[PDB]
Each structure stands twice: as structure tokens, then as C-alpha cells.
Length: 51
Length: 405
Figure 1: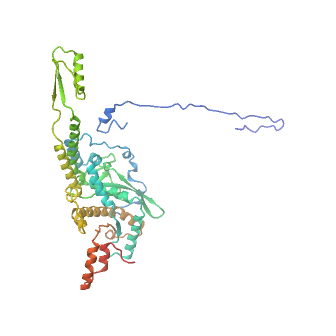
Figure 2: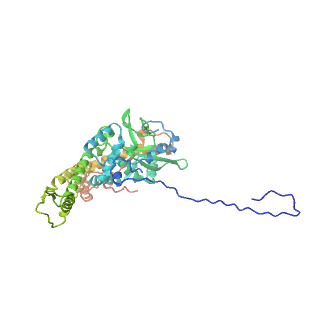
Figure 3: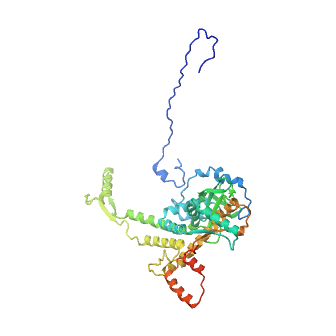
């Protein structure tokens, strides 16, 4: 942004804006588990399949 | 208030009762039909008698899904009702105000979307013994409206420990939760006299379903074994493991392979695999299917089919006995439930005053049976020439033709 009002219109002093930047990497996140194909079918109680 | 007299508070109508029970909406059916044995079925039924309706409801859902004959019968029975025309009539010798109330209710039901879905959801109580449909109440200014009808699974409820005929929500507490007034349309058709747990038709139909399932599975297994014979190879002492494996593979592939050679010291014996017929299995399946047909739709048209044969009185012959009785019973029970649950809140919220409960309008289904126009049209002229003064109202009502306006 712009700085304070100075105290001299005689011999005015120029200024510049500062360009700021922020860099961030969006790396992935994961998590998983292994299960057997027969066991999910060989489970009549409803558990092992709410996975 | 409601028909039962329980105090009614409009504050609780803004939100559904089950909204504060987000746990229920995340549940999945346990599918108790898979791996079901007669002992397991008996335990399920007995536990349901004691207030554990979750397992019974899930079993009934699986039974409906896994049996094509039972599903077809139930769907036909329900579609019979879904196709009936309906009307709202004012009470006996109603006054002008009552007639206006009935007319307004009729107009409101006509313009209420989702009525057919509501009827279909309610008819599930025929097989499950009880169906609960949650109401969404909204205000379009000064008049309450049912925003939508939500059918909640029967597995979401239980029995009151202090009352075996009163249902309650499953809120993790031993006593459950009482049903909110004006928040549900509970349909509980009564095929047999008893408690709510024992009142379902699927309770009657469970055993034939299990018989048919066992017969079909056994037949499928026997068809799998059918074909080639079991053949056993024998080897002498001093046969090494590699030769044993070679003999085993030869025997395993011998059925598919037309020819093979073995040493004279070995031997292969072809033994009977499975010799019989499908007659016992099919007999059991037919018995179970006939039982299901009789229990669902009557033993005059479905199981012991009425056969063909037309005629003017053929409609009456096919319908009046069995089919008309069942249709009228189901329609009357559904109409009573609707008049009790949906018509009354609309009358007592959307209109001024406190009309007496006995004078509430009643929803009526059109059970009129098509009458032979030709025979009766032949008959009238003789009677009128004789001198009888038959009213025109009876004719117009019975023929289905409307009175001139």
C-alpha cells in the first residue's frame, strides 16, 4: 500500500510499490488398506465392507 | 389436536423429528438373509416378537429382493390399489360449511404432488406390518403445507417396553422415543389379529421362501455336479510322488479327455456322480410358490388359477369372490389411515374453528365394479313400462355415468 503523507511538496520524493508473493505446493495426501476378496463376500454380518 | 386427543404444538412442526438423529441416516442394512438357516429364522422371528424389529425388517427387505415370485405377487397387489380412482366425501348429511371444507381438502389433495409415492410407501405395511412416512411441514404464508413425504425404514423403530402395540424411534435409549404427533403417517394393515410384530404377511411367507431357497440352491449344486462321473485312480506300492501327481492330473483331465493310457498295474474306476432327477426339488418349489400365491392373492385366481372363459358376468365371477374382497379391504384400510393422518392435520391447521372429530371428511376409494350396460339397458324398459319408478340417481351412480349439470 501507499506510505504516510510526507512533509515536503518542495523537492517531492518519489517512491515505489513493493510486489509481494507467496508460493506453496499442493502435494497430495493418501491412506489405504488391503483386504481379501473372499472375506468381504464371506461376511454376512455387515462389517468388513463398511470400509 | 389430533384424532387421538394428544396435544398438538405447532412449534415442533418446523423440523423433522429424526433431524436430531443424524446417526440413523448413516446406517447400512446388515442383510440377514445371506446364510440363513431355519434356526436363525426362528431366532429372528422370536427376537422380533420381543421388540427387536431391526433384524426382522432387514430380513423382510432381503426376502422381497431375492424372491422373484413373491416380489411379483406383492407388486401386482400394490399396483392394484395404485390404479384406483379416489375422492373425498363430506360426512353423513353434512352442512354447507362441511361441504366447503371437504371440497377444499379434495382440491388440496388433487394439487398435492407425490400422492402416488405416498400410497406406494404406505402399502409397504401390508408385508412389513407397519409403514412410517415422515412429513415435512412448511408455511406458504398463512396455510400449512406438506412439503414432502419421506419413507423411513422399518429398521429405524422398535417396540415400547411397556407396550407391545406402540412403536418408537431408536434413539440409543432403552425406551426409544415416542412418535411426534402430526409428524408421521403410520399405516398398519391388520391381516391377522395380534400385536404389531406378528401382524406382517412376510411373517407368514417366510417359511415357504426358505423352503424354495433351499430347494433352488440344492438343485443348482446338483446341476453343477451333473455331467461327467467321478473316477478314482489307484496306484501300486513303489509309485513316486511325481508319478502320483501325473496320475492325479490324468484322472482330473480324463473326463474332458476322450482317451488315455495307464500302466496295467494301475486302475481307474468310474463311479456314479449324481443320479436322480429334478422332480423332488421342482415339487418343493411348486408347493412353496402355490403357498405364496394363496397367501398373497388368494387360492382362486393365482395358485389355483381361474382359467379362461369370458362373458358378461365373467368380470363378476373373476372379481367379486376373493379379488374384490381383498381389493376392498386394502383400499378401505388405506383410506382410513389417510383420513386419520393426512386429512385431519390439514383440516385443523388450514381452516378456522375446531370442528368435531366425528364430522371430519373421509377419503373414499372408488370401488365401483363395472356393471353390464347391455343387459340392464334391456331390463329397464320392461320395468318402467310395468310401472316401477326407479330413481335416476341409482342408475347414474351404478353405471358410472355422471348426473347432468
